[PDB]
Image (cartoon, coloured by chain):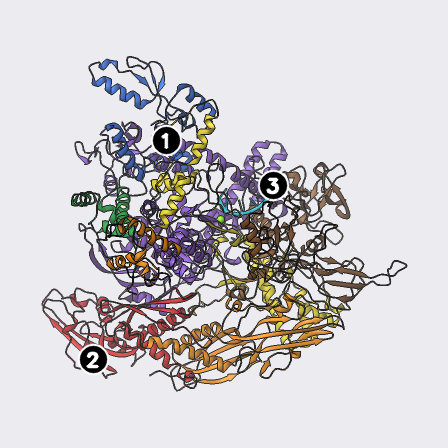
Chain colours: A blue, B green, C yellow, D orange, E purple, F brown, G red, H cyan
RNA sequence: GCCGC
């Protein structure tokens, strides 16, 4: 992150443009998903998968008695084009690059969208889970969890 | 007429919840079954609700309680 | 004055021909003013011809040679009446007038050499502190008009496909709310504004009429539904070999 | 304790140029009277201007007349510059007929009773062959400011025939005004100012009369600061309720429910009006049937209900 | 639907929250509202009657339309919306005409100017949408840019010029050492002409201090100043020092005083202060009567001597080359270097002549001061122009060549006040065309980058209050070799400390942990000698499917810490991608 | 899309579109000419010894590159010899100092590198080239006003543009003006040159108000009065935006350069009311509307003054045929031409028979398809151009 | 139609405290707001009668720069305080008032000797603070009437410096106006749209009331035009 | 093809 922030800021500072470093670090974070697996024991073995799913699964496995089940992982770095096409929502990433490449894999895998992002809800026509629509999305989540 | 809602924002500080609270109060005053708690200066129900929030006599909790009291009355 | 122009537009644009044209137009109109004043008092043709000759042969070794000596007496009068408004100067593209020549033409017209005069405020009568440049400039009216560029729509016709309003004036269309506009609305956090732009008031066939009825009734409640464009997309994708569905 | 300016030494350079002198003035008043006078005189002075024209053959402006050198638009633009001084009237008609050769000018406008052409050498048209004639009727009105022909519509209250040639009216006889303050020659007083006003006009308004008019306007406007002090409509509604020709049972029911006007009734919903005693399901439709023939559905919403 | 469009003009009478709407656009954008009000007031019983009445446009319809526009905000948007400032909310003011009137203070944020630009109009016909427009999207709400935190709604151009002209001094002017009881008296004397803004005189002055906890203390002290500075002091709100106005206010002091007012006083006062500043700047810029004349471009007298000496170097170096001891590269590089040196020397001579051009006598003998040259005032104030533009106008046009990137040996020794040759103009056309073609091609490359950034970052919302993690990143000033570009304060302001900050004295801790750092804390740590601060970042949030509000500092658009539900990913993408159109490729 | 050094006297390096077509659309320089093969040429003056000669040669890009060509702004003597020994020239895509003898050719004119449109910018050399591009481009968007006004400051190229464009009326064999009018000019040709037999005179029909491709107005007004001598190539009548044979596409404004209370902020322009009152910058716009009648399966489509289900008020301005009177002022949705199309009906219902009994024979069965003015269009009837098919009855108008 | 002009009606006056007022007049014809506001401001800011302190005589050093005998306030500040003192002189062209004070305490306007023909509007106006010692201060100030504002450019009275030392060259503010400002806004009446709305903001020394000052200014301006409105009177 | 970037 230090290398990316310093390198990109050199271009901007040379021309006299002021941008806070938080914005560059926000986009580096989106580049640091999709960790690989170099272990096993938790139904993961040598594959590229979401970092958040690994940490959530490891915490559950470590919470129980079988703490050794938790799998060691190696974090990856993707480009902005390659990371945006690797999202778990097929409705997005089919509205961005090529639909045929994404729609073909989604049909074979038989995945679901679950409409958790801003782009997905914009296409459908629902209130965004951000801003004034953030509260409305939270209330619906409790009802789904409570049945 | 209120150019700046800062006071209303700071009364309950989120800048998002107040927009909803004011929408609820404005629906109450516009659709029916409610009268303003502040003098009405020929201005719209939106700014009336915002001024009521700024004066400190309208918040989400009181809307919840007043609703409970009026439901128990019926 | 007829027009007031901002001085700030000149130095950052490097439009120095503006100022030189203004100064030379001031000089030309000054010469025309002198001729007009002479014609008003019905002065005899001899000295009017003398002044026209003096104005024509001014400069620093210019090629144009004109002598009123070979000019008819009546033709002198006609020429003087034709250039009564101002003297039409001509400065070729890369070989033209210089500052000194403009200055001596200004002197011959009995005008300040700097090209700046004293001006007074029309509302208070007070004199402006610094001298303000005043002259004559050639101004054009272009083919861009508000009348040909003023459009407003509340509700009109809609495309059969996607159930979305048409585009462009001369068709009573609506303004396109593009992708960057939606990004800006997302950045603000204005979810209800975005939902009212994305759904009803665009492609919700029932939502449009319900919203119109509510507004006429003074209710102001969106009651949003599902856009027809997404239904068109579902039908288009199903028309391939792919089955796409909405779970409950 | 202040000296009052006097109108002295009014000298007239030309038929249009003139000079007006106000000899005694205090220290600062020179400009206060001046700038105010310049603004009043440039903004609001009365005058007379050509309002519309009626040429024989021409019916619009984008045509041409055979034997006439200029277009109708150029003739109208020439007539816009015609300066006249009428007395006792506001709608004189200036008939003009001239057949032959040479430029046609105001001079040969038919001599009206009380109408003065200030400059009769103002050309308006040219004739180019012997067997050609021009005949036109010119309407002159009195006004105060710039009134465009397109902006006025009350003239269209009565339909104008095809053939009118209306022209924008300016009505302002003043073209240029300059003023300057000098030191008064009065040596007994320590220091006094003298105001000199140069006005260039079209020859229609007198200089002294213009100054008097401007001063009167200023005084009337100042009169307000001298003592500032100060410190359910539509005819179908509001109609008698016994105009619907209802049945007998409705008459007592409407009286029982205090329904006496038409507007108050149309504010009643079906579900709440049914609760009224002995209203009747069929009789309710009779009420709706009659109000439907008028176009008045039940359930309307008025804002204020007056006693009348 | 409910959309409009036309050309924009300027409205200087407008308040910041106001915009001028053509009355012909309204009555169409608000037709259903007009129908509802017509039917509600009893003027029309049926919808057909209301439609017919609106079609005829009677006067009562115009009265109803004004009430419809009495309290309903509207949105204006400019076509290339690089950022959310692309569309802003306003309260419409009905005008007679066909062009939208726009406030001059929002033009920079819109990147708009009045030479043919058009905007779109949208109506939020919902209680929720109206409130969102009033509470989130109004112009008086977004004053700080959500990219660096600096004020985006600031005076520029004529406002800056007028404020700069008002707050200047002259060594000898009408009034000298005059003592006045009040700034209003200085304004009264100035209106009488007794007091001169350039003239420097002493007036009784008072100040209010917020040092007392939530209280302002009066402080009346006679001070040295000028008439114009005292006159401008009448606009400043209470709680600001008098030292803020005893300066040129060169367009940087104005932004600084706006920022200090926002940080000390709040939003409603700063919004007013900005409106008052724009009004008074316009008025005094008009009163100054600034104008541009051919004589303002002063060519230094020694320019021809430098040109002749450089010509002598070129001839001698070429002779050295003709003798055969100099290679082509050596002579080419040397000629380029000496032409650059001569250009620098002539530019320095021009600037030195034009800076202190006014040699003015005093009460005794004669002095020299900063010049009142109009072009120099325009450049110095920051209103418009720079040194490079002026150097071209009065000094050499310089060395330039862009056929393939090389440099032509003989430069353009003529400015724009003097003419160019056919050859010199033909040479400059190469660079002109290169720039104009670069402008119309780089725009796509920037838009594609913005699309990719937005699509990668759109799924980022603040969904937590505090994750409690101890991870962070070290923050140090950006020092390159021996030169520094970014102090620690800029890189640290508005961030939350991951660890305690210790002074060089051991055990001692100046600041606590998990604490947002603001102007007071940054000033406190600037007094000491702390060089590295550990601050938590979003790359170590430790929260899945979102970030915490503590790992993300304050939002730059509002001094407070960011709230839950804010789409930070779209903000970051827009703030990175809004420039790039101005990046030189 | 870049400027090439061989573009010197062939294509102007100023005039070109801005956004997508920059560098791909060009204009000829004022002196440029094309080779028989099809290569651009530019003229130069030959130089023999140390003196230039008035003989002129046209050289292509290769031809110009081969010789050392001097600059247009190099001083000369009475005999034609350069005042200064060392002169500036172009040898091979470059420029440097050469002796006068070294030069083989000289630039005919400085404008040689400027387009005709750019040739019209006074003080062009004091303007930025990229900025000048904008001025040259914007010069071609100006609309002619009510009255043409000559430039007070020009460049001397206005007469060439005005005459060579074919907009004015130029005396082809001018003699002496015999008759003048707003629509015609008749010239009695001089007897010194004549075609034997039948003698002859010259008739010029000046163009009156007419639509242009951009809906502006093109009009011609005479410049001669009566009995005026006329030579060959003289201008008799000037067209749109022309004043006595000079290109006059704008007006001369008295301008002050100052800020005025924020009303000229950015590029805003503050205009006085005297400009509006004097009708400067007022233009005439002409529009064309057409109505066609075609036979239909129901039957022929007839054009008539009578219209079913329309009040007398809409028929006030119609002729007996059913067309707006010449000179009528029309606004909104007024009726221009009255046309009715037949409907299809062969089953006479008793109600339909009743409708035919009380009302006219057609009983308004024929639909209304008439030419109405579109909303937002206010116009005055100027010219009607009825065209009739061979065989069908001629229209009354 | 002609000769008839719009007159303002329902004018609004907003009085703040007792020396600040805000007067609004509407509607006005186009351009008349600027005319009226400028004329009224000019006369109010330059030609209005009133009385003000013009000369000061302090016992001790008579130089412009003086040691002030340890009075804790510079003589410049003393002259500044006496400059703002407002008096109402009755039936006198000039009058001399003497104030002497002993003992620690602030010297107020109520400490001046009592004259029946001179009124002090702000007796709590502070002239000089105590020397901080049991010292005695003697002052001799004369108030004279005049017009407008007369800066102390020079005395040009008596001979040599005899009058300048006696006068001490105190700036004279005869006019009882502290600030006068106007703004012209947009107002519409019936179908007309281009009318003026005039807003006047004035503050006063307290000798006169803002509205009374407006009345006096308009009165003298109207009386200046009598020689041209008399015969041409309705 | 043009306009605003
Ligand atoms: Mg622009
Ligand atoms: Zn965190």
> Splitting the image into 4 quarters, where does residue E208 fall?
bottom left
Q: Where in the figure is residue E139, as x and y percent of width and height?
A: 35, 49
Cα distance in 3D space between marks 1 and 2: 81 Å
CA neighbours of label 1 inside 10 A, class few (<14), some (14 to 19), many (20+): many
Q: Is residue F388 left or right of residue B69?
A: right
Front-most of E363 and A8?
A8
Q: Is residue E340 above or below residue E267?
A: above
Q: Which mark is residue G96?
A: 2
> Splitting the image into 4 quarters, where does residue D102 fall?
bottom right
Q: Is residue E326 above or below residue F138?
A: above
Tag 1 near tag 2, CB within 8 Å: no
What residue is pinned by disc 3? E315
Q: Chain of mark 3?
A: E
Q: Kindly indicate whether the residues beneath marks 3 and 2 are on one polypeptide chain.
A: no
Q: Kindly indicate whether the residues beneath marks 1 and 2 are on one polypeptide chain.
A: no
> Splitting the image into 4 quarters, where does residue D225 fall?
bottom left
Q: Where in the figure is residue F112, as x and y percent of width and height?
A: 68, 47
Badge 2 marks a residue whose secondary structure is strand
Q: Where in the figure is residue D92, as x and y percent of width and height?
A: 57, 78
Badge 3 marks a residue whose secondary structure is helix
Front-most of F233 and A13?
F233
């Amino acid at each position: 992150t230090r290398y990316i922030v310093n390198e990109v800021q050199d271009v901007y500072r040379l021309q006299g443009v002021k941008i806070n470093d938080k914005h560059i670090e926000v986009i580096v974070r989106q580049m640091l998903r999709k960790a690989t697996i170099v272990n096993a024991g938790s139904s993961d073995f040598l594959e590229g998968e979401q970092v958040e799913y690994s940490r959530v699964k490891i915490a559950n496995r470590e919470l129980e008695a079988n703490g050794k089940v938790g799998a060691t992982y190696s974090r990856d770095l993707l480009g902005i084009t390659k990371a945006s096409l690797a999202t778990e929502s097929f409705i997005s990433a089919a509205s961005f690059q090529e639909t045929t490449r994404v729609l073909t894999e989604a049909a074979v895998a038989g995945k679901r969208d679950e409409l958790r992002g801003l782009k997905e809800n914009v296409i459908v026509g629902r209130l965004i889970p951000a801003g004034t629509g953030y509260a409305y999305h939270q209330d619906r989540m409790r009802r789904r969890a409570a049945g | 007429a209120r150019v700046t809602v800062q006071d209303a924002v700071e009364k309950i500080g989120n800048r998002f919840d107040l927009v909803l609270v004011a929408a609820r109060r404005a629906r109450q005053m516009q659709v029916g079954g409610k009268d303003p708690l502040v003098p009405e200066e020929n201005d719209k129900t939106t700014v009336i609700a915002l001024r009521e929030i700024e004066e400190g006599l309208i918040n989400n909790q009181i809307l919840d309680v007043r609703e409970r009291q009026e439901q128990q009355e019926q | 004055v007829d027009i007031v122009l901002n001085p700030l537009g000149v130095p950052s644009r490097m439009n120095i021909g503006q100022i030189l044209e203004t100064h030379l137009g001031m000089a030309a109109k000054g010469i025309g003013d002198k001729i007009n004043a002479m014609l008003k008092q019905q002065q005899e043709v001899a000295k009017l011809r003398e002044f026209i000759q003096r104005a024509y042969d001014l400069g620093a070794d210019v090629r144009q040679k004109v002598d009123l000596s070979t000019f008819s007496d009546e033709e002198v009068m006609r020429l003087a009446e034709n250039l009564r408004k101002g003297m039409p100067i001509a400065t070729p593209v890369f070989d033209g007038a210089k500052e000194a020549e403009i200055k001596e033409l200004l002197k011959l017209g009995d005008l300040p050499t700097s090209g700046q005069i004293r001006l007074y405020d029309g509302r208070t009568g007070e004199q402006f502190e610094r001298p303000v440049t005043v002259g004559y400039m050639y101004m054009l009216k272009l083919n861009h008009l508000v009348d040909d560029k003023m459009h407003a729509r509340s509700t009109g016709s809609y495309s059969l496909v996607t159930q979305q309003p048409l585009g462009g004036k001369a068709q009573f269309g609506g303004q396109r709310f593009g992708e960057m506009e939606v990004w800006a609305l997302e950045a603000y956090g204005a979810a209800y504004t975005l939902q009212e732009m994305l759904t009803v008031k665009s492609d919700d066939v029932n939502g449009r009429t319900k919203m119109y009825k509510n507004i006429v009734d003074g209710n102001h409640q969106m009651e949003p539904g599902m856009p027809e464009s997404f239904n068109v997309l579902l039908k288009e994708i199903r028309s391939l070999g792919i089955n796409i569905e909405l779970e409950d | 304790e202040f000296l009052k300016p006097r109108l002295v030494d009014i000298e007239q350079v030309s038929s249009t140029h003139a000079k007006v002198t106000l000899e005694p003035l205090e220290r600062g008043f020179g400009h206060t009277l001046g700038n105010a006078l310049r603004r009043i005189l440039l903004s609001s002075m009365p005058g007379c201007a050509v309002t519309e024209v009626e040429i024989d053959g021409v019916l619009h402006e984008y045509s041409t007349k055979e034997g006439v050198q200029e277009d109708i638009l150029e003739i109208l633009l020439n007539l816009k510059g015609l300066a006249v001084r009428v007395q006792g009237k506001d709608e004189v008609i200036l008939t003009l007929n001239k057949s032959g050769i040479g430029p046609v000018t105001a001079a040969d406008i038919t001599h009206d009773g009380d109408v003065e052409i200030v400059k009769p050498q103002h050309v308006i048209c040219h004739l180019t062959d012997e067997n050609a004639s021009i005949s036109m009727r010119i309407k002159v009105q009195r006004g105060r400011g710039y009134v465009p022909a397109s902006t006025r519509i009350h003239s269209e209250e009565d339909e104008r025939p095809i053939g009118r040639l209306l022209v924008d009216a300016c009505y302002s006889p003043v073209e240029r005004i300059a003023y300057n303050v000098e030191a008064a020659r009065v040596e007994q007083r320590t220091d006094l100012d003298k105001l000199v006003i140069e006005m260039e006009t079209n020859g229609t308004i007198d200089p002294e009369e213009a100054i008097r008019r401007a001063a009167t306007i200023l005084a009337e406007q100042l009169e307000a600061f001298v003592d500032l002090r100060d410190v359910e409509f539509d005819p179908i509604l509001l109609r008698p309720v016994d105009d619907l020709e209802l049945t007998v049972r409705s008459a007592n029911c409407l009286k029982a429910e205090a329904i006496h006007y038409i507007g108050d009734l149309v504010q009643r919903t079906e579900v709440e009006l049914l609760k009224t005693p002995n209203l009747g399901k069929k009789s309710l439709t009779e009420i709706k049937d009659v109000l439907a023939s008028r176009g008045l559905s039940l359930g309307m919403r008025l804002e204020n209900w007056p006693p009348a | 639907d409910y959309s409009g469009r036309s050309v924009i003009t300027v409205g200087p009478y407008l308040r910041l929250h106001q915009c001028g709407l053509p009355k012909k656009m309204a009555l169409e954008l608000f037709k259903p509202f007009i129908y509802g009000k017509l039917e509600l007031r009893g003027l029309a019983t049926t919808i057909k009657a209301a439609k017919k009445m609106v079609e005829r446009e009677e006067a009562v319809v115009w009265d109803i339309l004004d009430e419809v526009i009495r309290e309903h905000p509207v949105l204006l948007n400019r076509a290339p919306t690089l950022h959310r400032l692309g569309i802003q909310a306003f309260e419409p003011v009905l005008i007679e005409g066909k062009a939208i009137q726009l406030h001059p203070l929002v033009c920079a944020a819109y990147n708009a100017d009045f030479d043919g630009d058009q905007m779109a109009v949208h109506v939020p016909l919902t209680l929720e949408a109206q409130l969102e427009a009033r509470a989130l999207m109004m112009s008086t709400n977004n004053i700080l840019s959500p990219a660096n935190g600096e004020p985006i709604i600031v005076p520029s151009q004529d406002v800056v010029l007028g404020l700069y002209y008002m707050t200047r001094d002259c060594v000898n002017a009408k009034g000298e050492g005059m003592v006045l009881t009040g700034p209003k008296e200085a304004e009264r004397l100035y209106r009488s002409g007794l007091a001169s803004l350039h003239a420097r005189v002493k007036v009784r002055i008072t100040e209010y201090e917020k040092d007392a906890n939530g209280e302002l203390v009066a402080k009346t002290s006679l001070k040295d100043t000028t008439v114009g500075r005292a006159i401008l002091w009448m606009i400043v709100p209470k709680g600001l020092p008098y030292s803020i106005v005893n300066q040129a206010l060169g367009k940087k002091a104005i932004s600084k005083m706006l920022n200090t007012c926002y940080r000390i006083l709040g939003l409603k006062p700063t919004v007013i202060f900005a409106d008052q500043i724009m009004y008074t700047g316009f008025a005094y810029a008009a009163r100054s009567g600034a104008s541009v004349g051919i004589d303002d471009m002063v060519i230094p007298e020694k320019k021809h001597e430098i040109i002749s000496e450089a010509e002598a170097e070129v001839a001698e170096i070429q002779e050295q080359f003709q003798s055969g001891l100099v290679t082509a590269g050596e002579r080419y590089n040397k000629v380029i270097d000496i032409w650059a040196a001569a250009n620098d020397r002539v530019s320095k001579a021009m600037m030195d002549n034009l800076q202190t051009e006014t040699v003015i006598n005093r009460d005794g003998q004669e002095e020299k001061q900063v010049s009142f040259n109009s072009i120099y005032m325009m450049a110095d104030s920051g209103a418009r122009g720079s040194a490079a533009q002026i150097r071209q106008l009065a000094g050499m046009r310089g060395l330039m060549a862009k056929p393939d990137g090389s440099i032509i040996e003989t430069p353009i020794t003529a400015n724009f006040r003097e003419g160019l040759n056919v050859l010199q103009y033909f040479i400059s056309t190469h660079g002109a065309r290169k720039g104009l073609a670069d402008t119309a091609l780089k725009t796509a490359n920037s838009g594609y980058l913005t699309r990719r950034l937005v699509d990668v970052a759109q799924d980022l919302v603040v969904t937590e209050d505090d994750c409690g993690t101890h991870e962070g990143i070290m923050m140090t000033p950006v020092i390159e070799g021996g030169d520094v570009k970014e102090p620690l304060r800029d890189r640290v302001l508005g961030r939350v400390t991951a660890e305690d900050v210790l002074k060089p004295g051991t055990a001692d801790i100046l600041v606590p942990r998990n604490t947002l750092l603001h102007e007071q804390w940054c000033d406190l740590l600037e007094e000491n000698s702390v060089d590295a601060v550990k601050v938590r970042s979003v790359v170590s949030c430790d929260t899945d499917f979102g970030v915490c509000a503590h790992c993300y500092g304050r939002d730059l658009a509002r001094g407070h810490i960011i709230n839950k539900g804010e789409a930070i990913g779209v903000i970051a993408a827009q703030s990175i991608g809004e420039p790039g159109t101005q990046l030189t490729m | 899309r870049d400027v090439h050094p061989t573009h010197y006297g062939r294509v102007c390096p100023i005039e070109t579109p801005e956004g997508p077509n920059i560098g791909l659309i060009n204009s000829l320089s004022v002196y440029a000419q094309t080779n028989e093969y099809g290569f651009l040429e530019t003229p130069y003056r030959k130089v023999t010894d140390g003196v230039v000669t008035d003989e002129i040669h046209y050289l292509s890009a290769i031809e110009e590159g081969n010789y050392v060509i001097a600059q247009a702004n190099s001083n000369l003597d009475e005999e034609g010899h350069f005042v200064e020994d060392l002169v500036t020239c172009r040898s091979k895509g470059e420029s440097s100092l050469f002796s006068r003898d070294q030069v083989d050719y000289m630039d005919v004119s400085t404008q040689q590198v400027v387009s005709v449109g750019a040739s019209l910018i006074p003080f062009l050399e004091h303007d930025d080239a990229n900025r000048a591009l904008m001025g040259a481009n914007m010069q071609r968007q100006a609309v002619p006003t009510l009255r043409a006004d000559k430039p007070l400051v020009g460049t001397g190229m206005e007469r060439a543009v005005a005459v060579d464009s074919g907009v004015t009326a130029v005396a082809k064999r001018g003699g002496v003006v015999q008759y003048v009018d707003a629509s015609r000019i008749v010239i009695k040709v001089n007897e010194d040159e004549m075609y034997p037999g039948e003698a002859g005179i010259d008739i010029y029909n000046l163009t009156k108000y007419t639509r242009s491709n951009q809906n502006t107005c093109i009009n011609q007004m005479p410049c001669v009065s009566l009995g005026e001598p006329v030579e060959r190539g003289d201008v008799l009548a000037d067209g749109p935006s022309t004043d006595l044979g000079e290109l006059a596409l704008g007006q001369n404004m008295r301008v002050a350069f100052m800020p005025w209370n924020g009303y000229n902020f950015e590029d805003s322009i503050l205009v006085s009311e005297r400009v509006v009152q004097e009708d400067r910058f007022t233009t005439i716009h002409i529009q064309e509307l057409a109505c066609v009648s075609r036979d239909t399966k129901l039957g022929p489509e007839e054009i008539t003054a009578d219209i079913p289900n329309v009040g007398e008020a809409a028929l006030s301005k119609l002729d007996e045929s059913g067309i707006v009177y010449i000179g009528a002022e029309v606004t909104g949705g007024d009726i221009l031409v009255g046309k009715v199309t037949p409907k299809g009906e062969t089953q006479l219902t008793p109600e339909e028979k009743l409708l035919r009994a009380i009302f006219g024979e057609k009983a308004s069965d024929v639909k209304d398809s008439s030419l109405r003015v579109p909303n937002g269009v206010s116009g005055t009837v100027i010219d009607v151009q009825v065209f009739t098919r061979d065989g069908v009855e001629k229209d009354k108008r």
